[PDB]
Length: 148
Ligand SMILES: *Sc1ccccc1C(=O)NCC(=O)N[C@]12C[C@H]3C[C@H](C[C@H](C3)C1)C2
Image 1 (cartoon, rainbow, N blue to C red):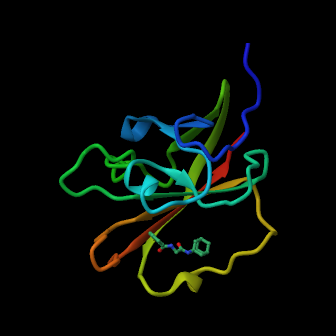
Image 2: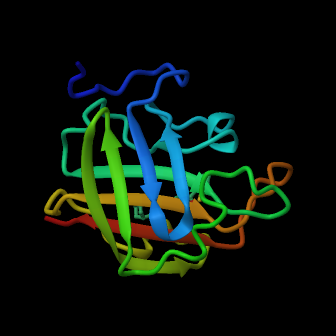
């Protein structure tokens, strides 16, 4: 049998599986802190807390250009009323993409963050990425709130 997984630093393990049927997405999420390298290899958490038991789950990723091998390349299809399945081991947590918008760069304080939240996965999918100069023309923020 299995159990509730924890969030380690090792990026070889899978703590959760991100599955979005509308976008045919079925990709492993790489648990741990955010590192520039790993965020170019797949999707990892932005939260420094090893707790996936918390209601605030921030995950970071990158958009698609020439490479369809990014875990959210087809995220363009998914709508604000689709189903985001965050599978932790065997437990399937369904979230709805209630809050979707692609905002402008520079301003990280475009939205006010607080600890008064619901169960939401806060995915930071930068809709651009030049590693050379370290720039991105857009940050597409996607917040999925837990459904029952
Ligand atoms: S998209 C990207 C890629 C690499 C480094 C940094 C970023 C980036 O733009 N991140 C900043 C960011 O999204 N900041 C937050 C701050 C608050 C309010 C929003 C949602 C979340 C908590 C991340 C924007």
